[PDB]
Amino acid sequence: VSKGEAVIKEFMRFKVHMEGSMNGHEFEIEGEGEGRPYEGTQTAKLKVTKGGPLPFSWDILSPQFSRAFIKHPADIPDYHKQSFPEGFKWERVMNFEDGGAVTVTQDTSLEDGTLIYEVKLRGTNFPPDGPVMQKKTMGLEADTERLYPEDGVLKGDIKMALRLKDGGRYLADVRTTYKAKKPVQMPGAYNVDRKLDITSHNEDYTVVEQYERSEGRHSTGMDELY
Ligand code: NA
Ligand code: NA
């Protein structure tokens, strides 16, 4: 626990705005959320404000809507919670098994006690007849982010799996750098286990609600072939 880290309260709200494009199609999202940052739980309500109804799966967007809301055991310091009031940024690459590619950048700030999220997304090389652009996915399976500290940043990697409507999994590798806007006490390497659910949506996905539970843990031990 660091001095000033109690600016992240037991209950916190956020506002989010995304500007994005998928295979050259521009869109925008606006939303709001809330959660229990020390319990690792949160919800959000998102609305499509431009480019709707989206001609692609919501599951591409859902992991882009909140790093203050991760539970930690007592001996893993919270990189993101310590970054306040200044906050942090992140830079992500998603590489899908069929060659779809997504670059995402994000800014997190704090204004009058509310967390402010600005997201920029560019997706390219999605097969037009693939499960993303045909809207044939059915949410994210629970996954694990392996995080390690380097040069005052955190580097994360996720083996991500989207459920397919017709059965089976559609995989991605998701690599992200997380960058505090000031120096903070760094954790060791550790894992974040996560389950993100779409709890409700209107028929055309112009209004979407999501929930996530995120928990930090140690690894038990890595660079093995099998
Ligand atoms: Na998160
Ligand atoms: Na879901």
Image (tube, rainbow, N blue to C red):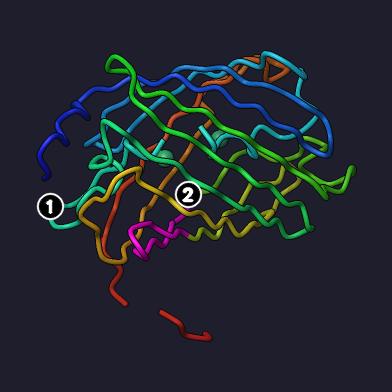
Q: Total label count?
A: 2
Q: Position of residue 161 (x, y in %)?
A: 60, 53
Q: Is residue 82 left or right of residue 197?
A: left
Q: Please tell me which of labels 1 and 2 falls first in the chain.
A: 1
Q: Position of residue 108 (x, y in %)?
A: 41, 32
In this rendering, the answer to whether 189 lies above or below 115 is: below
Q: Mark 2 vs ligand 2: CB under 8 Å?
A: no
Marks 1 and 2 in Cβ contact (< 8 Å): no
Q: Is residue 155 left or right of residue 58?
A: left
| Residue type at the position of mark 2 | Ala
Q: Quadrant of residue 218?
A: bottom left
Residue 27: mark? none
Q: Which residue is at 31% across, 48% downward?
A: 215
Q: CA–CA distance between discs 1 and 2?
A: 23 Å
Main secondary structure along the magenta-highlighted residues = strand
Q: Position of residue 115 (x, y in %)?
A: 36, 24
In this rendering, the answer to whether 75 lies above or below 127 is: below
| Magenta-tinted stretch | 142-156
Q: Residues within 10 Å of mark 1 (few under 14, many from 20)?
A: few
Q: Which residue is mark 2?
A: 142
Classify mark 2: helix, strand or loop: loop
Of marks 1 and 2, the one in the foreground: 1
Instruction: Assess whether residue 40 is covered by the magenta stretch.
Output: no
In this rendering, the answer to whether 151 lies above or below 47 is: below
Q: Which residue is mark 1?
A: 74
- From this viewpoint, which residue is outermost toward the right? 129
Ligand 2 resides in the quarter of the picture at top right
Q: Which residue is at 60% across, 43% downward?
A: 104
In this rendering, the answer to whether 54 lies above or below 92 is: above
| Residue type at the position of mark 1 | Ala
Q: Is residue 58 left or right of residue 214?
A: right
